[PDB]
Length: 283
Image (cartoon, rainbow, N blue to C red; front, side):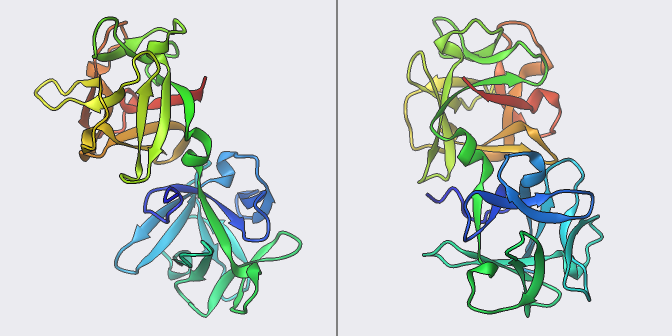
């Protein structure tokens, strides 16, 4: 899959090449360590690419906003407040075939991140050892791909993304355990984004472009209107934003932030307020 590619603004588990059950873990307000995967937010890392430097910040997703930092001139690493230090940027270069990634410090690119036998991390000069090779796995793909899900608006604990009765229009509705409210989320390799298929009619969540900007169930199409970048909120891994590929500044949104049964779901310009935030759970 291309779902684990090192895209800007995606959130990852970062694992040692020699153990797919371990991940980079923020264990305290300063310390990182390899730990058994628990899929907690302190084990999830957002990539923020800096085009000028051709290097990335690596930000923990537990709400603290701290970033992976080389404690120059020492050999240690930590999570620290972002002060835009050169020591807080990292080249992420990948071997296309092995999929291994070398995490190389921007301030001193002679130094790469290394994991030790005792699960600690440090920077070191480069060898040929797999103790400097990491794998990156996209968290959302690991969790939701090919899964039957429900999508709750953050506006109300009992309002869900639902196909309306006898209509293609998608609206909010309280949970009634209907196939109209169950969505199979499937990653599409060609578009590098997701479709969401309504269980009741096997048709897909699609932006219908006109002045109303409603989402509807629609037949399969190659058009970008049917494809969605599903992401966590910028600094909250418990909630999701769904950006439409036809215009990625526009997102799945609840009309006028209303909560009544029947309220239109639409695609509108991003602001990040609660009417654009969704709670995705596995059925």
